[PDB]
Amino acid sequence: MKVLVPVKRLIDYNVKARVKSDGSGVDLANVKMSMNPFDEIAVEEAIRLKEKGQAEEIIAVSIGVKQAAETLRTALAMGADRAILVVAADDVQQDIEPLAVAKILAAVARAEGTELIIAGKQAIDNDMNATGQMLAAILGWAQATFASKVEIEGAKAKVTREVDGGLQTIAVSLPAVVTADLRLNEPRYASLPNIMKAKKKPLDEKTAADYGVDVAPRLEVVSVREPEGRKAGIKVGSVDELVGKL
Amino acid sequence: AVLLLGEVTNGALNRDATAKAVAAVKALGDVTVLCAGASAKAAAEEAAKIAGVAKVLVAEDALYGHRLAEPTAALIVGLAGDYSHIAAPATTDAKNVMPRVAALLDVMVLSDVSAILDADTFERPIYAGNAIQVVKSKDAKKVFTIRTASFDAAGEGGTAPVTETAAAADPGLSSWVADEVAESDRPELTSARRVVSGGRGLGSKESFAIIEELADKLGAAVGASRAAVDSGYAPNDWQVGQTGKVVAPELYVAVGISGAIQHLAGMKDSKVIVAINKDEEAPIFQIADYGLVGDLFSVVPELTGKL
Ligand SMILES: Cc1cc2nc3c(=O)[nH]c(=O)nc-3n(C[C@H](O)[C@H](O)[C@H](O)COP(=O)(O)OP(=O)(O)OC[C@H]3O[C@@H](n4cnc5c(N)ncnc54)[C@H](O)[C@@H]3O)c2cc1C
Ligand SMILES: Nc1ncnc2c1ncn2[C@@H]1O[C@H](COP(=O)(O)O)[C@@H](O)[C@H]1O
Image (tube, rainbow over all chains, first blue to last red; front, side, top):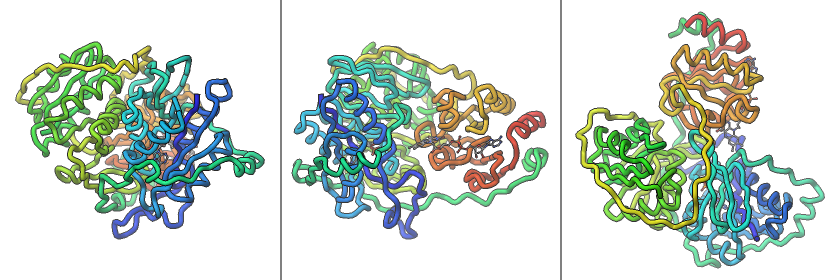
């Protein structure tokens, strides 16, 4: 089967988002961008499936601005067979909504003939945690969210999910969308020769209109402010002074 | 009106979450709670007793056992016609089904709403909580999850409204196989007024007990960082942060936690944060109201003893 892997380009998870002092948005202007942590997990799992003769091809897709290509090449470097880049935004500040992304991935998934999709749990930038589900919904497919282990076997998969309380294992029909939790696996690092090799792999630069999708925001962002800065904080000197400071 | 998905588990309604949700949304119209599950009856009862719930709907059917995203999302959508606001507490059960529902109605979803400014203007934390964005849904139906940790669970004395029954629909795309439930005999993390979390500084699963002792002494719930869970010190269920549970008790004691952005995301809203780390430069000491620099293996047991 062909596995589809949606990956996103967003701020480096170690960088503290700075908020412009006029509610415009997070100042992404000069910050280090990288692949969404959850997506690297996704890729790594897809690749693992290939190494067991479950998947034949692995398509990596990313939607956003031109520079997203760097993220795709990183995926190709890890082991992805090919990539597709759907340009939809003209500036890094315009984050496209999970609804738009879902409708695009749905067209891509239908066109490339992918039978399994593996997305991250959530994008560490919008913290939406909704794309995968919206995708399964639009396609009319089963879904396994917050996957910790995926035992794909036959025309169905046994995926144990990281749920409140503990773990919950379910079984879904094969044409399904799976989202990865941070505990699914330990992603590999793209080595120099493979990064160079990745540079010669296919990467189809498409556009949102190619799939006949309107990337208009259902949610107008009126503003975005900095969170409440907490009041100082004292550094005490002994357990007594601690319990004795209320 | 407003349809709200009741947070029920093993036939037992999680009153705290459902309460906080009703409390958050009551200002939008008549709150009507939906209890779906294999044993949703008792839950429906407790649901009705909450102050603000106009009415209660019950969908007790084996088809809703564990609330599989496919069947459940079909239920909600089939009822969505009479509601302009469909919400639920931001729990895994809600996060699994809500987005699917929204897509079916071809409408966006507002995840982890921390403030409802009105019928269509909402506030939600982005970038692991480093920014608060105020959005306005141009949608016809507002589907969203409530960040319970930002509201108060109002209730206990309600008008005991109606308790009806609903139908069904089953797209046979999934089935539940097994469950691995974590033994939690203390205050559930999301509801606790006091939380004591352990990080990597603990070194072992054995030493995590000193964290638990202090917690019991304070009648607090136990939290944990990724490090602690990955190393096997505690079940992932106790993870506080952007990947796990986001709490906001009165007291949050972080012992042996450096204070990584991802961890702060789930506890920067706590009333009083106390940190005890041996590294005077750990990020945690920049958000902690009261911090103590020392060896957790000498301070914690002394703290527990003078409590
Ligand atoms: C996308 C993503 C999501 C994540 N989500 C989460 C999340 O939800 N929650 C979460 O917790 N993490 C999460 N993480 C991991 C997170 O980034 C941090 O790496 C993690 O929180 C660090 O754990 P720690 O503080 O236990 O360990 P460290 O950062 O190693 O800190 C250990 C601390 O122990 C102190 N210490 C050691 N011994 C003692 C002692 N004897 N006495 C006192 N102090 C001592 C040390 O000085 C240090 O401060 C996520 C990561 C990613 C990529
Ligand atoms: N712009 C995008 N491009 C590619 N994949 C995306 C994009 N936005 C979201 N996704 C996928 O959907 C997952 C969840 O994102 P979110 O729904 O925003 O939390 C991401 O981790 C990716 O797998």
